[PDB]
Length: 143
Length: 142
Ligand SMILES: [Mg+2]
Ligand SMILES: [Mg+2]
Image (cartoon, rainbow over the protein chains, first blue to last red):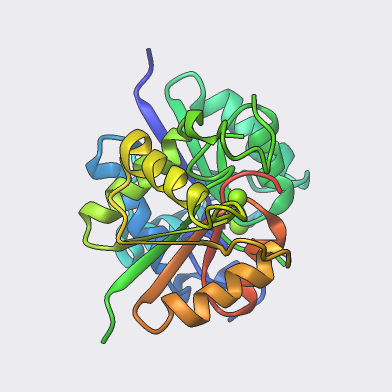
């Protein structure tokens, strides 16, 4: 009986989409998506553990966690999401989001949490969560 | 300065979809979609006005609000959702869900509420909400 959890995505979900999508160097200035961010705070107060998962590459070759650290600072200090765990696509991983996010899920999250719900904006990712038996709410079209 | 509201759909959203659509008298025995129903309680507690909107025809030719009243009772008594307003397809309206729900929005919801969010399951409707500038979360495939 693992503690109950909710997974949130970052891009398009917690954070709005102002810059280039793969231009992570400017991602520290992203704008919060208010209802989704409020949702994460709501779930945390209700005793769900919040887990953040992003397809953002963690960094560059010379700085492998550069973007992970930027993302984390944005989530924690700008959005104020009270997460207990953050997971990203490792530097050099070029597979599709749904493939990576599924791997992250089975390897790092599922053994520790009982994930009741995932929040995301991309159809391919949304269908993956649903397919492996995780309720998922799509919060935007994803285009 | 209107009160903030969240719109919830009923079929496939608040209620799981053992019964057929348009068989609305076996409708009283629907089972809750728990994460969504819990959401509506949370929002209500956080001071949002809960507005339930549904494509279900409101009743029969003989009784124009028979189905409306059945839906209302399930939402209030079984789901436990503290709603403030309920809007459905009028008896004998045969237009599409998204045309009906949009007309409901302009005439009965938008004048009284600042709608911050709509929760729904059907793609055609979800697209309508986003198209008219209302954030919408799609909680299952449609
Ligand atoms: Mg995203
Ligand atoms: Mg529906």
